[PDB]
Image (cartoon, rainbow, N blue to C red; front, side, top):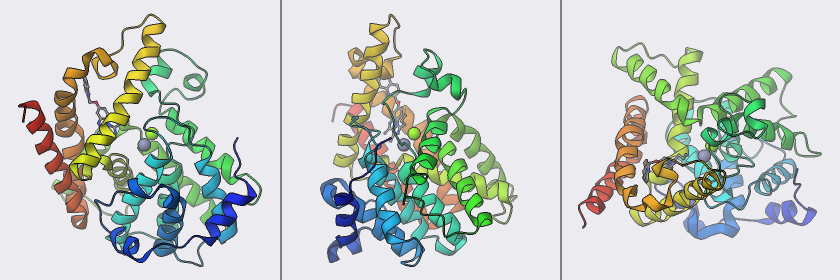
Length: 322
Ligand SMILES: CCCc1nc(C)c2c(C)nc3cc(OCc4ccc5ccccc5n4)ccc3n12
Ligand SMILES: [Mg+2]
Ligand SMILES: [Zn+2]
């Protein structure tokens, strides 16, 4: 497992954020894209702002973040950029719904988002379970996500990395649970059930944030919303991100071909033409319903729904040749 150098976490301690970035970070549609060098410092800032400067021991935090960074691989999409992207969206939702969530939860959720794709390979849970690869035997379901959490704990177990040590064993065990459920929730195979339950609970008015299982379900949908948030950016960022995703999908399809298996059209680079229709279907069946139910449960998150509506509109425009 990769460990940051002495030169990386200390430099991060030194980092400060420009004034104009402080303002824009608060926007849902903010794109971290153009600020690569500043990405670690952006997360620190977000953590300090959301949780408090007294929250974690700075030195332990810097080690943790820079070591998380080194455990993201050089893959087209499920990389370090994705991790910070997802953490930022979480920060925006949390800032607009601050007191609905406890100190511990905001700490856990921010750290969970950063680590939620730790050591991703560019391969889906479908690939691994239908090939093997020991990970699918180690985790029969949810599968990469179980691996991501395993990695999260491993990095915490590195010397001077455990940011949660100053917590009482009660709060400590809780924050791990928060992180575990939240990371697992990022398996999209689970999202569909989750959103139906939440839809059912909201429409009937059963929904109660004092109810832990309800609260667990809300957190998981927030995770889905953050995980998918590239659909909520300005169109050219969304379109550029779509390239990265397909780069990974097609590379998975290519390894499948090498091993004598036909991949689905989504992972088939020969089926490039079907992308806009595939996107349209993803927005209609996944993204739109996600951000709709989210807006219902958390009204301040509506700009997320709006941006996704806008991007759906764009994909429709591509389909009809415009
Ligand atoms: C697994 C990553 C989840 C995810 N995060 C984002 C942020 C996206 C985004 C933005 N788009 C996604 C599109 C998908 O599949 C859609 C699809 C379905 C059938 C196809 C057939 C041929 C060509 C492309 C197809 N695409 C599947 C997952 C998508 N996705
Ligand atoms: Mg994932
Ligand atoms: Zn992800």
